[PDB]
Image 1 (tube, rainbow over the protein chains, first blue to last red):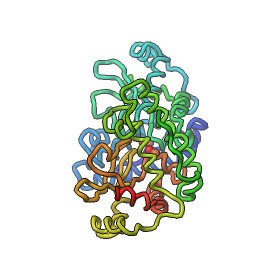
Image 2: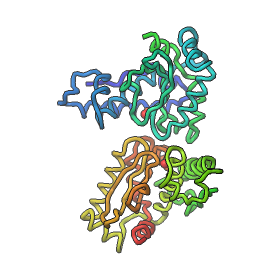
Image 3: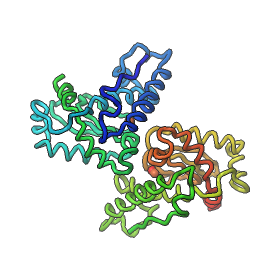
Image 4: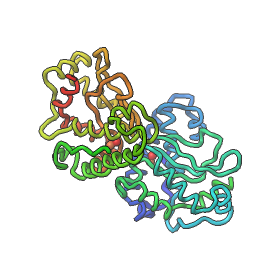
Length: 192
Length: 192
Ligand SMILES: [Fe+2]
Ligand SMILES: [Fe+2]
Ligand SMILES: [O]
Ligand SMILES: [O]
């Protein structure tokens, strides 16, 4: 069965940008529950033995929602880090400048997309199959994995991701997200 | 321009079932923001002169999302009250018993639907135009007003409705919702 991968840092490592309490609920309750529900829903089914990505690309309904959310959250935790944030360098910086005009342009576009992604969902930096970077949003458990675009960076805009720390101020959460971005992970994703 | 209608009670009236803090944010920030955003989108447009309902039934995208949420929240506050809850009497009791067998069955079914509603949204008791009652769930700003059916009761299951008080425990929030239901309002809705 699928297991909840260990958080890449201590539960308080993202403070004050994302609190230890947010981590305890978001990781320990929400993410854990998606793992448990996924395992239960796939027992005895043709989805047993399949990778998480394989399930995401071949499922609908509850199986999809849980599988995609498991993957999305693991991806999200890796997108964040202590002692990180700031501006990317190298190939990531160059690709962002080429695709959006500048890092500042990208940051504003990503922020705007995330803030205006209505309801629950995720906002993504992806590499489209044309080789160009783009910002796309998804609803609920939706993920670029069901397309031919490669996810590079994401922000969870489900209210549970930020409500403890920012209440209604999703834009405040976005401001603090930038202080946490793990560009090393983004660079790995782009290089792949 | 649209005004945020006054809350039917002070912000502590629903406590401890829904906290004063929740109401301060939910009414004073979320509901207010929907009003502000709606006004900004419709100013100087052909949506001026239209009632809230007329906008909801003739719009899409941002105009729709904001107009529907303004209406949904006003309806929600009217569905809740101090010194209420328990079970309906008279016409409402009769109608629910006729359509669901018993109030207890209705209560279980409504609760189940509300807990299963994935992501942000609303769960409703409606009266169809042939008089049948039904439980329906909607996503995000979705509302029975865009259908033929008449809303009788709703619960908001956006995480902002409960996260301060219940965190991830949406079922706890639902339990406490029942302690607040304003059956007088439900009766008005049914009698219209
Ligand atoms: Fe999440
Ligand atoms: Fe709400
Ligand atoms: O999420
Ligand atoms: O909401």
